[PDB]
Image (cartoon, coloured by chain):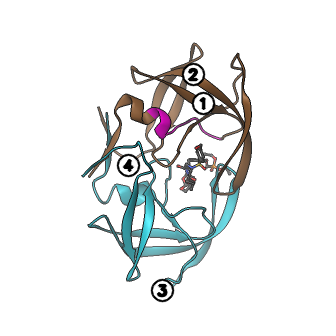
Chain colours: A cyan, B brown
C-alpha cells in the first residue's frame, strides 16, 4: 500500500510464529527487534544509534512477514526502544520512498 | 521522485543558507541536524534512540528545502552523527512509503 507519515509507520509483522508491531524505518540499515526468544543459532554483535551502541544477538536468514509481505534476512534482537524494520528487509518487500 | 532503499536515502537539503546532506528517515518523529549555529531562540530537549539520549536545541519554524521541496517546522540541533529528516518535515514534501 501507500503509507503516509502523519503518524508513525507502524505495521504488524509475524516472526517466529508470533505477531508484533514494528516501525518501518528508512533511517535504519538493519532490522532490530526488542528482546524475544528466537530459535536457531545467533552471534553477538554491536550496533550504534543516536545515543550510542548496544549489544544485540544476530539471527541470520530469519523468516519474517511484514504487512503481508515475506522477507528472509538478518534480524538483530536487543534493547532497542522500538521494534524497527530496516532497509535490509524493506528492500526485500519492495518498499520505496516517493514524493 | 522515487528513492529505492538499497543505499541510505541521502539527499541534499538547504537550511540557514547552507547546503547539507541528510537522511530521509521515516523512523524519526522529528528532524535532527548536526551541530550548527542557527540564530534565534531555542528550547532544550533530550531525544532518545538506540543507545540512549542526547541533548539537543529545539528551534521552531525553521525553513528547510529538501530536493527542491520546501518545508518549515521544528528542527532539533545537537551532536547527532547524521543529519536526519523526520516525519514532521517529510509529510510536508508529500513523502510516502510504497510497497
Ligand atoms: C552513522 C555513524 O554513527 P553510528 O554508527 C549510527 O548513526 C546513526 C544512523 C541513523 C539513525 C536514525 C535511526 N536509525 C537507527 O538507530 O538504526 C540503527 C539500526 O540500524 C543501523 O543503521 C543505522 C543505525 C543503526 C532511526 O532511523 C531514527 N531514530 C528513532 C528510532 C530508534 C530505534 C525509533 C525510536 S533516532 O535516530 O534515534 C531519533 C529519535 C528521536 C528524533 C526526534 O523525534 C529523531 C531521530 C541514528 C544514528 O553510531 C555511532 C556509534
- Whichever of labels 4 and 1 marks the residue nearer the N terminus, that label is 4
Where are the magenta residues, as a range? B81-89
Judged from the image, the secondary structure of the residue bearing numbered disc 4 is loop
Q: Would you name the residue on which mark 1 appears?
A: B75
- Whichever of labels 4 and 2 marks the residue nearer the N terminus, that label is 4
Judged from the image, the secondary structure of the residue bearing numbered disc 2 is strand
Q: CA distance from mark 2 to mark 1?
A: 6 Å
Image coordinates of residue A4 in percent, x first then y, are 34, 44
User: Where residue B62 is drawn, which disc sits there?
Assistant: 2
User: Where residue B6 is drawn, which disc sits there?
Assistant: 4
Tags 4 and 2 touching, CB below 8 Å: no
From the image, state whether disc 3 or disc 1 is nearer to you. 1
Tags 2 and 1 touching, CB below 8 Å: yes
Q: Would you name the residue on which mark 3 appears?
A: A40
Residue at the far bottom in the pictured view: A39
Tags 3 and 1 touching, CB below 8 Å: no
Q: Residues within 10 Å of mark 2 (few under 14, many from 20)?
A: some
- Compared with A74, A29 (above or below) is above
Image coordinates of residue A2 in percent, x first then y, are 26, 47
Amino acid at each position: 500500500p501507500q503509507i503516509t507519515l502523519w503518524k508513525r509507520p507502524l505495521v504488524t509483522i509475524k516472526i517466529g510464529g508470533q505477531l508484533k508491531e514494528a516501525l518501518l524505518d528508512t533511517g535504519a540499515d538493519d532490522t532490530v527487534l526488542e528482546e524475544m526468544n528466537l530459535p536457531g543459532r545467533w552471534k553477538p554483535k554491536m550496533i550504534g544509534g543516536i545515543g550510542g551502541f548496544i549489544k544485540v544477538r544476530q539471527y541470520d536468514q530469519i523468516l519474517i512477514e511484514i504487512c503481508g509481505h515475506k522477507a528472509i534476512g538478518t534480524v538483530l534482537v536487543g534493547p532497542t526502544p522500538v521494534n524497527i524494520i530496516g532497509r535490509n528487509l524493506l528492500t526485500q518487500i519492495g518498499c520505496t520512498l516517493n514524493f
